[PDB]
Image (cartoon, rainbow, N blue to C red; front, side, top):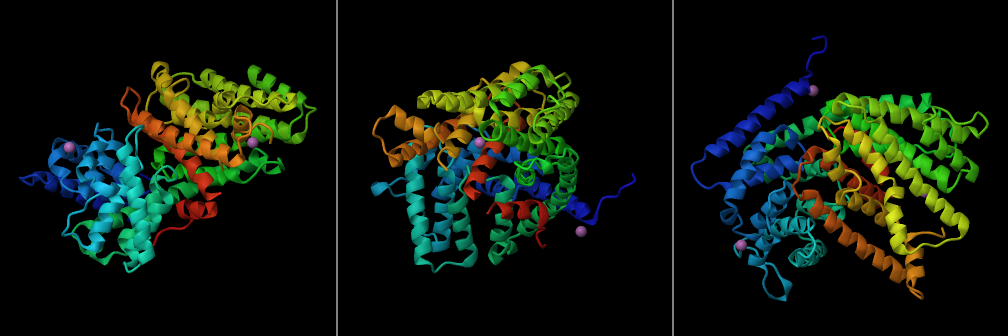
Length: 512
Ligand SMILES: [Co+2]
Ligand SMILES: [Co+2]
Ligand SMILES: [Co+2]
C-alpha cells in the first residue's frame, strides 16, 4: 500500500507473464517438441531467472524426460538434456553419451553442422561432463575431448567474439567454482552480444527479464548490505584489529544464489556467522592464549553473554559479537522452523570449537596426526557446517530433526560438503593436509602429496554431486543452499579477482 511497484518491477512482471505463455504455447504444440522446450528451460536457467518459472520448467522437463530417447538425438541435445535433467534430479544416465563416442576417444557431431554449431555442441558436452558421478568414465572422456577441442578452437581463433567469450567463460569457471548469478551475469553478455540470438523470437524478452531481475534484486541486496555494515560497526568488530572486511565478500557470495527478498535472514546470517567463524578460527590458530581458548570454550559451553572482563579487547569483542549473532540467527529460525533451535545450534558451534581445539593441542604437543585422522577432524574444523546450518534453518523449508539428520551432520551429504572445503583449502604450518600425508608416506615429495590431495578432491566432488542429486525427504531448497555454500568457497579460493565478484553482484548494475 505505502510503496508502489517500481517501473522495472512492473516491466519484469509483464515479461514473466509473456514468458509463461511461451512455455504454455510450446506445450500446446501438437508433436514432439522436446528440444524446443529444453532449450527454453536452458535460457531461463543460465540467466538465473528460473525461479519465476518453476511450474513451467517442471512441466517442460517432465515432458523432455518422457521423450528422453527421442530428444537425445545428437551430441548437443543429449549433453544439454543430460546436464539439465541431472541437475533437476531426474534419474538420467551418462550412458546417453556413449551413442556418440567414436574411436580415439572422439565424440561425434552431426556432419552438417556449421563450425559455430559444432562448437556449441562440444560446449554443451563440456558443460555436461562437469556433473559427473563416481565411475562414469564416459564423463572423464567427454571432459578431456571437449577441453582439447575448445582450446584448439581458441588457439585457431577465427571465431566470433561472443562465441569466443562463451568458450573462455565456460573453460575458466566450470561448475564447482561457480554460482548461478555469476553464470547469469556472463550469459547476459554472451547472449546479448549475439545478434542472431537476440533476433530469434522470444529471446529478447528473456534477456530483458534477466537484466531487469538482476538489477531489481541487486538493489534489494545492496540495501540489505547496509544493515550488515551497521552491524560491523555496532558490534565494534571494525576495532578487532586482527579481523578483516570479509563480511562484504561473504554477503556477495550468498547473493549470487539466494535471491528472493524474503530470504534476507539467510543472506544476513551467512555473512555474519561466516565472518565470525573466520574470526574465531584466527583466535584459535593464531591470536589466542591457550588459557583464553579454554575460557572461550567454557563460555560457549555455558552460553555466557560475556567473557571475563579481564581478557584482551580483541578476544572480548569477538565473543560478544559471536554470542549475539548466533542468538539473533536462532530467533529467525524459530519463526520459520516453528520451534526452538538455539539448543541444537549451540551443539553445532561446540562441535566446531572441539575441532579447532584439537588442532591447537596437536600444534601445542608437536603431534602430527595421520592424514585420515586430520581429514576426519578437518571436517568439523573447516567451519563449513557452522556457516551452513543456522542460515539454512532460516529459509521457509521446514527441517524437522529427523529430516535434518539427512542433511546436517552426521549425513554423508554434510561430510562431503565439509571435505570439499577442507581439501580445496589444503591444496590452495606443522599440521596440514600435505604434511600429514608425508608423515603417512615417508619420503613422499610435496609434489606427490599435493598431487594426491587434488585427486582426492576430484573424487570427493563427484561423490558430493551424486549425493547432492540423490532424492530423499530433504527439501531441495535446503540442499541447494548448502550445496551452493560449498561452491561459493570453491569459487572464493579460485578468486584468491574477488573484488570483481562483489562489484558485479552488489554494486554495478547491467545496462539494458
Ligand atoms: Co526502471
Ligand atoms: Co541409449
Ligand atoms: Co586459520
